[PDB]
Image 1 (cartoon, each protein chain N blue to C red):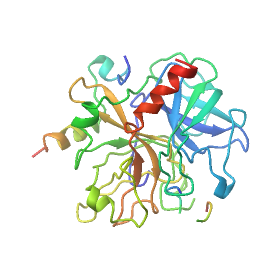
Image 2 (image 1 turned 45 degrees about the vertical axis):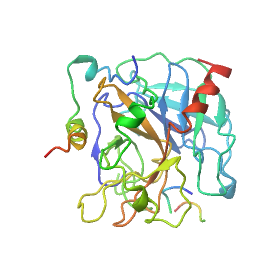
Image 3 (image 1 turned 120 degrees about the horizontal axis):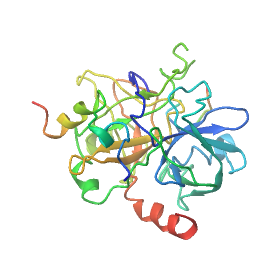
Image 4 (image 1 turned 180 degrees about the vertical axis):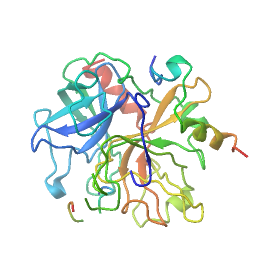
Length: 257
Length: 10
Length: 29
């Protein structure tokens, strides 16, 4: 994420790495919405246009991640996706609509001080925070600056950032893409005079808010797209983890826990 | 697309 | 038990940027 601060030990035990096994690399961030279930950004895994397309087989999932580099020995978790699940109405062709996906950790992940779920919004929670200027914080390992590459490449540790939902009207006019009442835009604006943005490979990463009600941590989004990274004039775009809360639901009780 | 950039990675 | 950072909330602790998060809501002045 552009213009951020580096996270802390435990500040996000739900962050999960989207680690293709080979090219032994990284392509996303996902979150722990269970003991054994994971969700993410659509495109993270199904993208024809760039012959993007995967399978449980291809990739491997990691947890307990402070450093993006090393092999966090006795803190990190690593499981294999038992099955993936895309949103049968996904749009790789249109505007990354329902940009959402989930992955039944093939086996069950036991929690600890670095791995602890996020909770799915309830229309109230979904209703109390989801709104103008009400900051929300994005996490991640992505690209420190607009598309390029220890240096302005990528961080050693997990970058944390916080941002203000934007005005739907304005959301819809920093772009030219048909945007859906399923997607929301985060990010400080121009004069607002501050910076912060999620960037390359930040995707499928969370937009969890703090519910002042039960002070519980709740994931309002799934990082989807944007036009660059921190450019005076537009904001990223995220997924209403809720509109689609229907689904997330529907398929977890059809194939898992 | 992705935040990245139509055209792939850089 | 979810939403409950077992090294912060789970024990009288708050991460150096969340307070920032709070203020947005009651529009911190």
